[PDB]
Image (tube, coloured by chain):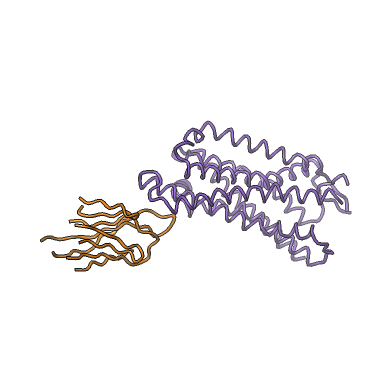
Amino acid sequence: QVQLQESGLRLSCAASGTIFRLYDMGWYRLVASITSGGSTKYGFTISRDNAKNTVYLQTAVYYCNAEYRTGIWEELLDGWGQGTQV
Amino acid sequence: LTSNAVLTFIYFVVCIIGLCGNTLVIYVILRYAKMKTITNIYILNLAIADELFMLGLPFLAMQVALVHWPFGKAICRVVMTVDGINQFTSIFCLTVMSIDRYLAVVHPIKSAKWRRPRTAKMITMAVWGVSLLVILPIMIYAGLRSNGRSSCTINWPGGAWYTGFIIYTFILGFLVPLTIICLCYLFIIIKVKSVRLLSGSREKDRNLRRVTRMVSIVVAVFIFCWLPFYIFNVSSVSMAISPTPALKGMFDFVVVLTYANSCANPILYAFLSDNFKKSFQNVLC
């Protein structure tokens, strides 16, 4: 249901579709993760802009991962993304 | 005459549908062991009330078919008692279900003691006892009024008693339960909207989110079916309205609208649930 697009050092992941809310997001090789309330946890620097649902991070493949609900009475789901080359 | 014939056909259709649905629900809850939970007790008691009303309705269908009431006074007493049970116990059961959902969703840690199969039966008995205490007056004053015709009605010792009865029912039947229900759900919504996981696992979260939505939809259907009746009663009491031929069709319409609700509830449990649908299929097929 959700769609995740990655760009490109500077890495950026953006989400679009039919979504209700967005919970913690992350970058996997777990390399980065940011809870919906800024509570980052590494193991670079990671930032998140919740106005546009975007996550930035500043060799191998790197994937993006998000968690979401499509409604208020629905189940928690998580969406993966494509790959990128460093 | 056409009006009497169509209102009799509608009464009999409603009676058959409701009897089948509620008998199936009661049987399924009592027979199987997977279907014994805390909410199904309240669902069972609601079904029992609707079954009693469905056993009573054919006499009212008869009375509206032929304008006479030929069955006596001992039957009149029982049909008035059942109509009161239908008006009051159903809302009391919905109120207890809503309070239970509030306790289950918002306070899972502290309220673990008040949710045990031994404590629900006491609350159901208290519901029935309070409902009977509220019904007592119409049980006392029910009787037969002679128009050649006779009718099953309530002969108030008077008028002022009618205007008192309208307010007594509007206050104990619509306002006080709806305020409590509205507060429970206003608090439930904020909690769901803010939390990420309700109970620590995705399965428990998913089940909670299904049951709460089912209960909310049942309550909304009840409100939808019972609002015009009270609007009409309070409007007729407040302002002086001289009876016209148009004042009978509206009353008959709103009354049969109220009666339809009992039939509606056993249909929702099939779409909005999965255990009930599985059990209905396993039994019928």
Q: Quadrant of residue A61?
A: bottom left
In the image, residue B38 above or below residue A6: above
Q: Give me the residue at 72% from left, 40% from top.
A: B134
Q: Nearer the viewer, residue B262 or B105?
A: B105
In the image, residue B260 above or below residue B2: above
Count of picture labels = 0
Q: Position of residue A1 (x, y in %)?
A: 33, 64
Q: Position of residue B51 (x, y in %)?
A: 62, 45
Chain A rendered in what hue? Answer: orange
Left or right: residue B263 versus residue B247 is left
- Chain that is coloured purple in the picture: B
Q: Nearer the viewer, residue B150 or B234?
A: B234
Q: Give me the residue at 46% from left, 50% from top.
A: B191
Please, which residue is most extreme toward the left here? A59
Q: Quadrant of the N terminus of chain B?
A: bottom right
Q: Give me the residue at 44% from left, 39% from top.
A: B34
Q: Nearer the viewer, residue B233 or B175?
A: B175
In the image, residue B108 above or below residue B65: above
Q: Quadrant of residue B250?
A: bottom right
Q: Position of residue B177 (x, y in %)?
A: 63, 47
Please, which residue is most extreme toward the front here? A45
Left or right: residue B128 versus residue A32 is right
Q: Position of residue B142 (x, y in %)?
A: 80, 44
In the image, residue B89 above or below residue A24: above
